[PDB]
Image: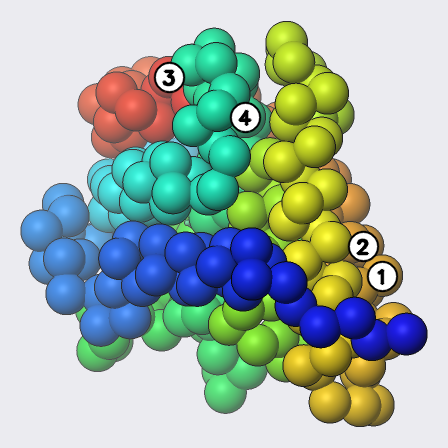
């Protein structure tokens, strides 16, 4: 069976596409406003040197902080999100922030050279640039594999935005009060996605794709946990707080 998208479902997709278009600048034109990226000579991938300098942290922390703000904006536009209490809204945002950033970054990720390309060389982020931000390969390598796998799904933008929405509105986040309401909202979203794939996504991908996308959400949980572990280590570095931002400190602290 391939039930047609209901008027409500079509409206949901429209709202999410619009929300994404208003919160994700494909030209990355604001990036020049972030603290400048600095790339020290670390061909050896020296953890000691990376931690001593954290040369790329101010820039990437600003990029992440900026992205969290955009995600907050996107989330507020998710149909039903505002029906939740502010406490639940914040619980969901803080817990999904890094995951949505990883998902949305797939738009700048390119398999041409396995980097996040957001402009000229200055705004091209490679594994080496992330390690220069004090991040561990224990996180970055799996992150890259995740990006490639997500790339290969060749998601329509409709699927991309629905996946980010579903990621955010997850009832199984620690601290949520009204898990029931959250699940109802997510189910409305998941049903839209499943319905969209079944009647709009041409094979060989008409089906099976929903399962692959849901698996990505599971992968994201592991990446989230891995990032939290690495962020903790990074936080031990003296003077690190100044290289981050208040929003970043709050979300991951
Ligand atoms: C942000 C966005 C972009 C890229 C994402 C990247 C590339 C650089 C390194 C990042 C920011 C990863 C880092 C492991 C996260 C480190 C954060 C912290 C220093 C606080 O522990 C996660 C996603 C990666 C650019 C654009 O796609 C908008 C998107 O929204």
Residue corresponding to mark 2? 215
Q: Nearer the viewer, mark 2 or mark 1?
A: 1
**Residue 206: x percent and y percent?**
81, 81
Q: CA distance from mark 2 to mark 4?
A: 19 Å
**N-term-proximal mark, 2 vs 3:** 2
Q: Are marks 2 and 1 in contact (CB under 8 Å)?
A: yes
Say whether marks 1 and 3 touch (CB < 8 Å): no
Q: CA distance from mark 1 to mark 3?
A: 33 Å
| Label 1: how many Cα within 10 Å (few below 14, some 14–19, many 20+) | few
The residue tagged 4 is: 92
Q: Check disc 1 and report its element: helix, strand or loop.
A: helix
Report helix, strand or loop for mark 3.
helix
Q: Which numbered mark, 2 or 3, is in the foreground of this view? A: 2
The residue sitting at 44% across, 63% down in the picture is 14
Q: Secondary structure at mark 4?
A: helix
In percent of width and height, residue 179 lies at: 70, 19
On-image quarter of the N terminus: bottom right
116 left or right, relative to 210: left
Q: Is mark 2 within 8 Å of ligand 1?
A: no
Dot 2 falls on a residue whose secondary structure is helix
Look at mark 1 in the image and give the residue it sits on. 211
**Relative to residue 222, is residue 199 depicted above or below?**
below
Residue at mark 3: C-beta within 8 A of ligand 1: no
Q: Residue furthest front?
A: 7
The crowd level at tag 2 (other Cα within 10 Å; few <14, some 14-19, many 20+) is: few
Residue 250: which disc?
A: 3
**Residue appearing at x 45%, y 19% in the figure:** 90
Tag count: 4
């Amino acid at each position: 069976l391939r039930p047609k998208l209901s008027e409500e479902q079509q409206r949901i997709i429209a709202i999410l596409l619009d929300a994404h278009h208003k919160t994700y600048d494909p030209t990355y034109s604001d990036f020049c406003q972030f603290r400048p990226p600095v790339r020290v000579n670390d061909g050896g991938g020296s953890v000691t040197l990376e931690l001593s300098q954290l040369s790329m942290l101010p820039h990437l922390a600003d990029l992440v902080s900026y992205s969290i703000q955009k995600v907050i904006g996107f989330a507020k536009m998710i149909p039903g999100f505002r029906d939740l209490t502010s406490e639940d809204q914040i619980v969901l945002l803080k817990s999904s922030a890094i995951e949505v950033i990883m998902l949305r970054s797939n738009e700048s990720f390119t398999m041409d050279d396995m980097s996040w390309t957001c402009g000229n060389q200055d705004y091209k982020y490679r594994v080496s640039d992330v390690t220069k931000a004090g991040q561990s390969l224990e996180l970055i390598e799996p992150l890259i594999k995740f990006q490639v796998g997500l790339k290969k799904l060749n998601l329509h933008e409709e699927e991309h935005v629905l996946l980010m929405a579903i990621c955010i509105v997850s009832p199984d986040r620690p601290g949520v009060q009204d898990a029931a309401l959250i699940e109802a909202i997510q189910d409305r979203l998941s049903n839209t996605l499943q319905t969209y794939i079944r009647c709009r996504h041409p094979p060989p991908g008409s089906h099976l794709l929903y399962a692959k996308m849901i698996q990505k959400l599971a992968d994201l949980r592991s990446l989230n946990e891995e990032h939290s572990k690495q962020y903790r280590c990074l936080s031990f570095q003296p003077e690190c707080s100044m290289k981050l931002t208040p929003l970043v400190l709050e979300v991951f602290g």
